[PDB]
Image (spheres, coloured by chain):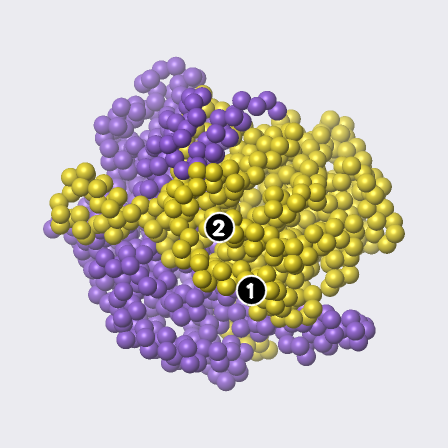
Chain colours: A yellow, B purple
Amino acid sequence: AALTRNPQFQKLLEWHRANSANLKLRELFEADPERFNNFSLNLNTNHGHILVDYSKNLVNKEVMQMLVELAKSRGVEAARDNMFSGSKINYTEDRAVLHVALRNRSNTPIKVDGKDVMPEVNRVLDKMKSFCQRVRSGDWKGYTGKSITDIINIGIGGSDLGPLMVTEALKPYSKGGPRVWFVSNIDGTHIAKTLASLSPETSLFIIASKTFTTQETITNAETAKEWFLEAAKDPSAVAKHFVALSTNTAKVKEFGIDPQNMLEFWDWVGGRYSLWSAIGLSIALHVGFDHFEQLLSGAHWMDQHFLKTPLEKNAPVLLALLGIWYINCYGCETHALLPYDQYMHRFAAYFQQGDMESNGKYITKSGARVDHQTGPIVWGEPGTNGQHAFYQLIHQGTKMIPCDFLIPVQTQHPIRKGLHHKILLANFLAQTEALMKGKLPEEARKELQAAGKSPEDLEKLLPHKVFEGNRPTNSIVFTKLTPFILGALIAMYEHKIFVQGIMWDINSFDQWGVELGKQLAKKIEPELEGSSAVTSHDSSTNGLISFIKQQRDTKL
Amino acid sequence: AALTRNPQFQKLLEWHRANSANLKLRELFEADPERFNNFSLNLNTNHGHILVDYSKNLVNKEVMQMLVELAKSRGVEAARDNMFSGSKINYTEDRAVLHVALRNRSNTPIKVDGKDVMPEVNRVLDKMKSFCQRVRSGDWKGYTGKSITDIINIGIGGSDLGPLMVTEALKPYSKGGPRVWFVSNIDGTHIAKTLASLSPETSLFIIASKTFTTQETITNAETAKEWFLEAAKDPSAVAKHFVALSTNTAKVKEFGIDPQNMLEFWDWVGGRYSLWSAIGLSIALHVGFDHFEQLLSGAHWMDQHFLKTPLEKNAPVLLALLGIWYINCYGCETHALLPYDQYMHRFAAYFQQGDMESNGKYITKSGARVDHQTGPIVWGEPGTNGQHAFYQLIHQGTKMIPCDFLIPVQTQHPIRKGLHHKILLANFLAQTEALMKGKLPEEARKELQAAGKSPEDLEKLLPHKVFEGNRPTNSIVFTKLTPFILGALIAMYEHKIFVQGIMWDINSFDQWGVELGKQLAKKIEPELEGSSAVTSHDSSTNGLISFIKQQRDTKL
Ligand SMILES: O=P(O)(O)OC[C@H]1O[C@H](O)[C@H](O)[C@@H](O)[C@@H]1O
């Protein structure tokens, strides 16, 4: 595997072995009054600032230099330039990787197979803009002559998580827009509970699927169409109530939607990088096309920051390198995303797909099996909720857990003259300070002494009250969570993921690991029908099927 | 540390070192046709069946025997009896641990300080019943004389997660009940967006907190009171719209709440074990007291199973033991909970608190620091959604991740003559089969050959298409997700957590690790107010505060 054979990596690992035990965050800060200044980036986007403070990490000047040299030796800059120029860097599928084209506001040509993609990107955006105007204005009418009140996105994974997360995060920008609903699970609860609250006369369905063959999405779409036709009783009315977002015109036609009712995207748009494309239609419908364009513009700003900045001062590069340090040198399995923002409640779930489906890989570009760790398990809940759930384990468990804490300076709801946001900010700051500093036995002893505890009760309680500290965090703070800033943040993590994949020599852009489960499910489907025993699998699968058939008709 | 010095543990570890590399799930099933039969428990509760199939784990007869022996020699049987009898097993706080008393339907006396707690448990339950009749019938009137249509639970952590997860899971049982809302985050978005959808005339607030001084909860509660009084304009009207789940009589009275409308619980009720207490009021209001009683009865059934069953066939003990094997022998940091049920969408988040805040610990009963791992990081999303987000990494990444797959046989929504549920079940079954079996080079090769790939393309793609398999799972299948069965499931995991804590020699029932962040936040809060530079912390905390003070003025 290319990483472990790399001499710059071996140097880093050797240094970690010899010296890492001596790194103490409390002491790093005491020895260096300039530590924050030297280990943070303050990015002025001209539409707000993003501060990436990486000073509370187990690093020094030497470590950062070694990490930057490693990025250089792994060819990160050339790989990046190849992505942006439309090279077919998705080598297992022989595809370009061009989510950066979707938000290329500059309109500089990007060629695939000698042909500029920007005219077709811009054509679809124009069509999206026109459609959003028609629906949001009340002009677009349903089959009984009423304006649309509800938009229902039907899709799963990449066709669900982005639009859901973004509409949730940008909820204050949705005033006067139609309601949005997301249906994703094949579990019939999902579509049933949604349809229960809706009228066929005023509901517009958006069928979102790159392939247009995904079982959950097509089944859900068929159920929706059946519910719709039971009321409308007119096949021609489908064109007023269903729109398709796909690359696969043939399958869209087969489902019963005309290409005029389809907004297209392309094979070089990965599903988990797709919200910037036609897949973002439900975002644009909910918040308006203007705000959708600002989302794209913010991503574009971050794209240019990634493209043009020297590695040592490049935000997604530094984030990627810190992650490699913890993954490949410290062996940490996980990475927590902890946004102190209730609107961002689905941000961590989004990056579960974005990170884990990209970099949860084990074969390199050479065909070699990796002999090192690749992508981490991503998880998290918004602050302050998480503090009262799982921070006990972060402070006093036995796992090292790199955390990114995120927060806007300005709240969308400055209620009680700012009291709530003041408290929120205080907790944001205090938690990373606590994780860094800890509490020494001598400090805990004095607290117990002052609390009026007896020598007997004191000694029994003391060790439980000690915080070992030295737990590293990033703090990412931004002026306000606007559409533009959100776009910049999402793109920043997209590029972090890219940099890590290149350093591991894996393909961040394929997903062969989902195929086997789909195949085995198609085999089991027919076996569930009827009351005969199944014997064709291992004894567990067979036994679970027996239980299902036995318990099917028990009237509880 | 006790565990590492235990001879049964050292034997298990030595066996792992010598033999674990040769455990292959495919081979284990091939060699033993009785495997499912001998490595599963089919529990008949008389109100449905719960099948705990642990056969797809990296264990054999000898391993389970070694594991059960370790549980015995770590004192699991004696510790359990001590919990059930009211012994003060929460040893750092000198407290009993009696969530089992809350649902003790048998009413067998359980004594704390020589006094039976059951009369008081039953009195509060009776008051809850009365409250439910009043609100649900429409007899409880708001300040303008109208029936209540909306219930708002205000609370954090254990005062929020349980009621939220259970009302979400039991949504079908809520017919005729008032709508329920949960406000928890201090982030003012949470209360603001909730109150915007509400009428002061028809909304009832439930303030959930032991001390009635918890900062986030009391601040949110005070904001709700202010909004209410803007419309009502009469301090005496508060008593018709605010109730408390608390013991602090004076504070509740000062708030304006009729002390009649305070429902009590006790210090032996841990927050993360509290939904079974007065804290469950919002559940009982939403689905009715009868269904709440069914929830308690399900937990009671599992309590009796845990208490009376020999270890080798005791469901929560076996789950705990498999966890110890993966944590302390294989070194797996995480445990995934994957319910194939949209109604269970908050189940994993609930057990983040239940598990991580319980067992994210590092000091043993003797005061010594553990020299072994304790509680895992718990995470997950409902199936099938997770398949399209992160299962790529579970199948083809570099992490070993024990997963529990959960599903009901019968759906609450059998739409399209059961087609959706048939598909859901097929995926549930197929994913654990896939994780176990993988896909061999010989199988992938035939697929590439059929696809018409060239010799060169076949060779290059082949390793990317192989699934190594040997990834262990539990499958937990149950007749239907009723209130009773849900209660049984929650209690099962409560007791799994308890068993692991005993084996690690830690206190599952305190939470000293949340204290430091609370102290540091209280110090920072007043520092944010004015314009002056803050220099009293480390340079990162100071620099982050400087950025906040500079950016809060910026106009975008
Ligand atoms: O957009 P679709 O063609 O319906 O595919 C949706 C999804 O399904 C798959 O399982 C893959 O995990 C993803 O890459 C994707 O987001």
Q: Is residue B265 above or below residue A532?
A: above
Please give the name of the residue rendered at 27% of the width and 23% of the height, measured from the top-left corner: B254
Cβ–Cβ under 8 Å for marks 1 and 2: no
Which residue is pictured at 30% across the width and 75% down the height? B8
For this orientation, the residue located farthest to the bottom is B31
In the image, residue B25 above or below residue A455: below
User: The numbered mark 2 sits on a residue in which chain?
Assistant: A
Using the image, tell me which numbered label, if any, was put on residue B475: none
SS at mark 1 in the image: helix
**What amino acid type should be assigned to the residue bearing mark 1?**
Gln
Q: CA distance from mark 1 to mark 2?
A: 17 Å
Pointer 1 or 2: first along the chain: 1
Q: Amino acid at mark 2?
A: Val
Q: Is residue A203 left or right of residue B45?
A: right
Rendering coords of residue B55 (x, y %): 46, 73
Residue that mark 2 sits on: A59
- Dividing the picture into quarters, in which one does residue B370 lie? bottom left
On the image, the x and y values in percent for residue A90 come to: 73, 58
The crowd level at tag 1 (other Cα within 10 Å; few <14, some 14-19, many 20+) is some
Estimate the x, y position of residue A338 in percent, counting from the top left.
Answer: 49, 44
Which quadrant would the N terminus of chain A be assigned to in this image?
A: bottom right
**SS of the residue at dot 2?**
loop
Chain letter for mark 1, please.
Answer: A
Q: Give the residue displayed 73% in from the left and 45% down from the top.
A: A100
Q: Confirm whether circles 1 and 2 share one chain.
A: yes
Image: A19 above or below B11: above
Mark 2, Cα crowd under 10 Å, few <14 / some 14-19 / many 20+, is some
Q: Which residue is mark 1?
A: A10
Residue toward you, A274 or B456: B456
Q: Quadrant of residue B361?
A: bottom left
Q: Mark 2 CB in 8 Å range of ligand 1? A: no
- Residue A528 in picture, x, y percent from top left: 59, 68
